[PDB]
Image (tube, rainbow, N blue to C red; front, side):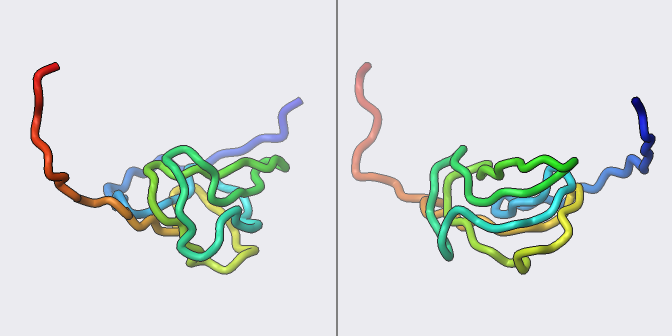
Length: 100
């Protein structure tokens, strides 16, 4: 049992902390959150189909998931799917460090 496959191994330094690229090829289907939907770091915001398998897509860092690419596109390794919008990029609360 072995069909066969091959590809190139190229590296590219370009991945913003507010971007949700595809870790592996597949096929975009739909999302599990509404426009600019807010979720937790780890929650699923969308899914995909790869190797005849449906895999869930989680956010690398809590924020707001938004659909950019139309639903039903070709998911490829190291590609763009949706961007994340940090809802808490900075917010110094009125309280410093205290004995522990």
